[PDB]
Length: 386
Image (cartoon, rainbow, N blue to C red; front, top):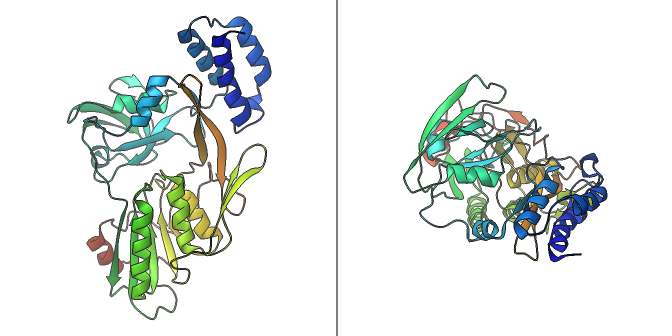
């Protein structure tokens, strides 16, 4: 057994042990391993890399890929530079014919500005058809020199005809995780049953990152302090990002019971529950969501709904429920692998299904800016949130 063969095996093993589906997409994982060891050239590192890649492909899971030591490192050093993008976070389609689609059009970003919406299929990036490419490959296409341009062609799902050809200028897009306000003189159409007052606390979590937690905490604390009659938690177009932030937020609102299950073809492998340490467990709550509501955000929504902590209003969410992790190799290289799936507290997959609203509403109706928000809520055509 050579060093190179030993390395290929670390990769094969990473999947053998961690993969989400222990039937390996109806393939004999073990048979593959032996076959490859006998048939695939692996005398030089570069070739062992090709072998791993070839191996990973049989699973037919676009999220599962191999990463070379440099790319891994660079992923890691990540976010920094004059490297800029177009305000687009991506993922693959919720039922894979293939497709790379928009996950999140960053608020006030180029893509956003141009009309790109969550869920839109990306056909090409500067002439190259992106279908089936690694998300890493795609990110690279969209990324580039500061203030430079790139052509993105997209179409609405199921309408390859209805395409739009975006000419985008690459620029850093700073984003804020949390904003909130108190809306006063709120219309009644918008108040929870029996509101002592016409005031709603509004909390906008546009993103789940490392800053979300502290800002959300503070927000709920103040609002509770003010005794608003109801809370509006807006997670529309929030790609999810940081899972832990999603859980911390949910613990702020739900004081007991289960929040989210981590499952695979084995059964439940892990679970996250309330820790009892909430900020507000009593003010009536409504959560705004939409098709751009994904991953950690959907976990939050699911927890709020299933526990009966709040109603869900808007339109069904993204349905992005897979969990990928990177397994590092001795190499310094790594295998990004899908290892689990989020399920709601009720035992339902987030993947494909998403979170469904209790109050079906046009998710467009409400603005995202504080002023505009209070304006629509305190008005004649204020949405019937509750």
